[PDB]
Image 1 (tube, chains in turn red, yellow):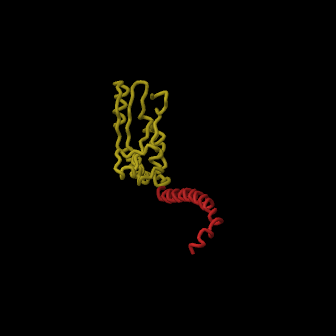
Image 2: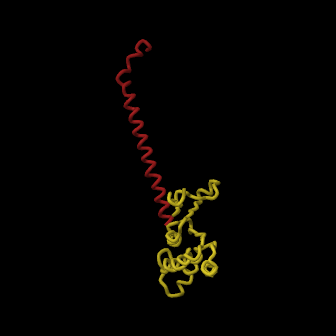
Image 3: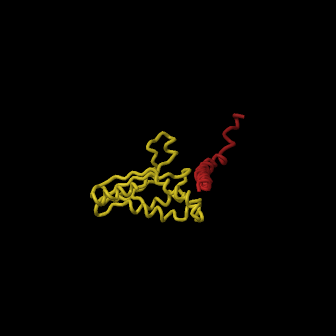
Length: 50
Length: 130
């Protein structure tokens, strides 16, 4: 039936919206951990700038 | 009636004939309308229980034999764009080449609105074609 498959198609799109977003979460959890080096090396350049 | 005329041209005249049918679904629809009054319990969706057998007898007559050849082109109506419906589905196994049209394709300005991902052909083999 089309009505039942309308929901199935709708859920089919939702099920992959998640995968693409999940891959984006992985993409943005690499760059967060790559830029975490600043956490260590900050808070000392701007001393006389204060 | 028309199929009988084509059969005569195929057998007696031994000619290669074309047979266009539009629409073959109405043959199923008409039998469903009378099925209720013949004392037959409706099947799923609401078609007659003899949907598969009645269509099969007609379709098998539409074939090319050793005497002649019939090239048949039949138009099938998919009610409410639901290709899971018993009538469209029952007709898929009685064909050598299926052309599935999609409304979404047409709405985008593409004509003919063919969905190549759903079509199929029996002669799509290297042995037959180049």
